[PDB]
Amino acid sequence: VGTFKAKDLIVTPATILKEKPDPNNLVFGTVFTDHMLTVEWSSEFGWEKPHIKPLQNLSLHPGSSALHYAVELFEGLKAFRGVDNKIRLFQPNLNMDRMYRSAVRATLPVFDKEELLECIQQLVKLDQEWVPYSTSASLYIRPTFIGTEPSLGVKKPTKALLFVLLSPVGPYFSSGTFNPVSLWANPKYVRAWKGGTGDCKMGGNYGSSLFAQCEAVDNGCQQVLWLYGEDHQITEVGTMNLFLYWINEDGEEELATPPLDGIILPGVTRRCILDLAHQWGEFKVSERYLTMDDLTTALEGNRVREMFGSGTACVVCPVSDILYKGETIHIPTMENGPKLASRILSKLTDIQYGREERDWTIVLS
Amino acid sequence: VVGTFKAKDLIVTPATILKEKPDPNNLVFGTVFTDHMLTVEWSSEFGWEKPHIKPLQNLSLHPGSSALHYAVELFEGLKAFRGVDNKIRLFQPNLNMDRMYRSAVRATLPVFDKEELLECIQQLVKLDQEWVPYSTSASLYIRPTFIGTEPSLGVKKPTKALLFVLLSPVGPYFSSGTFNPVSLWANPKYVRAWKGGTGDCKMGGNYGSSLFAQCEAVDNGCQQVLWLYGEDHQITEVGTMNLFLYWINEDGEEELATPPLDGIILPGVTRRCILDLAHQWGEFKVSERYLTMDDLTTALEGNRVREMFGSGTACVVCPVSDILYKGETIHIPTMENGPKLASRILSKLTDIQYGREERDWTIVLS
Ligand SMILES: CCCc1cc(=O)n2nc(NCc3c(F)cc(Cl)cc3F)c(C#N)c2[nH]1
Ligand SMILES: CCCc1cc(=O)n2nc(NCc3c(F)cc(Cl)cc3F)c(C#N)c2[nH]1
Ligand SMILES: *Cc1c(COP(=O)(O)O)cnc(C)c1O
Ligand SMILES: *Cc1c(COP(=O)(O)O)cnc(C)c1O
Ligand SMILES: [Mg+2]
């Protein structure tokens, strides 16, 4: 039981460097930088020294448990080139906390969160010219942790690989504006269950999503609204946390989001939005159950203001419609500004690009 | 695009150095691999490439491959058996091809021609046929595997995939080669699968989530997990195996019971074979029915339980001796009852697998 250390980094620079992309023509998660971080683990010898080396294919035994039994987890965070040309990470300690917690739940080996964050800092530093020269683009950082056990028994792995990829990305939507989405709400598909891994960023949570999203697209919708339970609770939207801004049953202005009862991924963006809403103290902030009946009752009383997803790749993604029980239900998000969604995006973007000082950002090592 | 690969297009790159075969008595499940593997690449742009049989070697995967990030992956498990007549047989391999195809559609992995995949698997086993053990208690495990190799990090249907097949010689699941009854850990805190989920498919995402509960079982002195579901603590599966209960039921009737295929149970090939045999014998009631922990503890207090066992490909029939539940150890008298039915099932399935009797369930290697 132990950790790799950043002071042990072995750095092998690429001798052929790739052209950087146009920061205005960027598709999320498609372009990769020159270098990656890799760290090997075995039960026999523990953590090997960490390597920063050229981006390359992984060489994996075909029996590797990541390939058979989804022994795998990941993270997602961003580096931003500030208005002052200082590169900043955003809330990276929250990602290290979540990745450590996911590793325990996956039965992958633990590591020192500060050692991994310093290894990520050194990788971004080497590839810093990849952090785009744009106030609407960023560098996506993908820490990934896989079982590489070369045996077909279903068991805790005795071999693993932790690696980090970098990808320059633009706005999630090419327009760089709000592209409000239609949601497909079919209770036939359930993303997560009590006693499952839905509250960890484990790869096994995401395999089911593709089929339901393909069905959404066949029915003229862009994303899945994940429903849970006999009362059709609204939980998450695609790969994003779900917020509802409304007048509640008590006549109170409220920002509501489902609570962390085991079927909700505790998003870093979700945490930030709840912290902002509590700080502003302008309306009620509630982690509470929201059902489709709660929503349709509110819509018929003109009580709904905004619905939006939260997540790293999109930040704030408004919802305009839900298809449920054969009816298209309009959500008036875009007819209400969307004032709160816009205020949140502006605040987070100002912090990310260093337009205001914050404890939420760390300058590049 | 090429809609499916064909076996007639197989490219064979033989290994030039062959490995020493293992002792068929000293085999740990899924640890030893044969000389060759099958690989077939797919892209949305061009469809399926030609299939390759080549030496076992590492895969070269883009680190963004969706199998590694979002568990875009599934597998199968089936066996080849060297008969008492030295003919190698497969056991209902078309059921595995059907299950794998159905899982691929649910995963959004590309379709393939099930007959062409089975012919490629036959050619791979034929090349590595000396790996099929010279033992009536050992077999060759076949692991078809299908992974998303999409390099991009969006959560989306893959535009690149790899279908591959590994072979692994395996002995009895336990080195003793006799029944090693297990103790089960029953904790309703963890759930394997749920209604609206993918528990009825061999998708890798069903297994990664299970390891934590298995580790908790082991540190509480148990070998396997009894998977509970719902407010009434339905008993569903035992480890990675289907669950059978042989008992006198609530109505006083001798009964072999197993949970029903309601979407949270893997539809095991061994499970369906056991139900088919039990219906054919007609010596007791055969029921696909819900079973709860209360049903089981009530039966045990009434001395109504005869045998409990798992069914699956790697073990065939795996008896259960004990369950740890609500802080108490509950003895299951499987081994004090022979176990007569478990032994009879094992003997019948092994007689079919090793060609001691003719069966529509076996196919001789082409
Ligand atoms: C898994 C981590 C990487 C990642 C991959 C991926 O494919 N997506 N897609 C995202 N947004 C699509 C989307 C939308 F555009 C709108 C709504 Cl309401 C809901 C929604 F999910 C986001 C985000 N944020 C994201 N992140
Ligand atoms: C996933 C497919 C490959 C595979 C991997 C693996 O680790 N196992 N372990 C198995 N048997 C352990 C076990 C037991 F020994 C006894 C009982 Cl009651 C329940 C049980 F699961 C079996 C079987 N059959 C199996 N198959
Ligand atoms: C990552 C993730 C979230 C939250 O994303 P953040 O980028 O941490 O805000 C929500 N739901 C799912 C399924 C996720 O994978
Ligand atoms: C593979 C598997 C079984 C057994 O299926 P067979 O086709 O008999 O090998 C049972 N339960 C689970 C969860 C499985 O993965
Ligand atoms: Mg054909």
Image (cartoon, coloured by chain):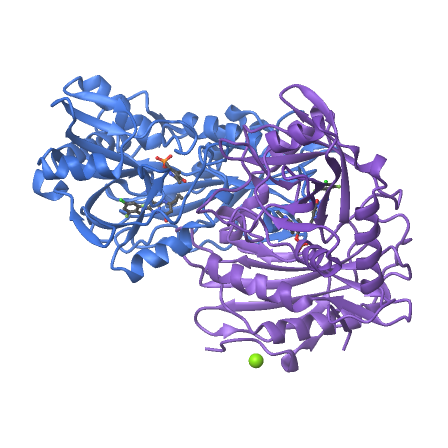
Chain colours: A blue, B purple
* Quadrant assignment, res A280: top left
Percent of width and height locating residue A117:
48, 29
Q: Is residue A150 above or below residue B91?
A: above
* Quadrant assignment, res A261: top left
Percent of width and height locating residue A109:
62, 31
Residue located at (68% from left, 55% from top): B275
Work out whether residue A305 can be spotted: no
Percent of width and height locating residue B149:
51, 58
Horizontally, is B96 left or right of B63 in the view? right
Q: Is residue B9 above or below residue B240?
A: below
* Quadrant assignment, res B365: bottom right
Percent of width and height locating residue B179:
84, 42
Ligand 5 resides in the quarter of the picture at: bottom right
Work out whether residue A190 can be spotted: yes
Residue located at (32% from left, 20% from top): A359
Tally the numbered discs.
Answer: 0
Residue located at (64% from left, 69% from top): B94
- Judge by depth and name the residue closer to the eye, B300 or B180: B300
Horizontally, is A74 left or right of A351 in the view? right
Residue reaching furthest to the bottom: B8
Q: Is residue A129 above or below residue B125?
A: above
Horizontally, is B258 left or right of B194 in the view? right
Q: Quadrant of the N terminus of chain A?
A: top right
Residue located at (43% from left, 71% from top): B45
Q: Is residue B10 above or below residue A114?
A: below
Q: Quadrant of the C terminus of chain A?
A: top left
Horizontally, is A229 left or right of B176 in the view? left
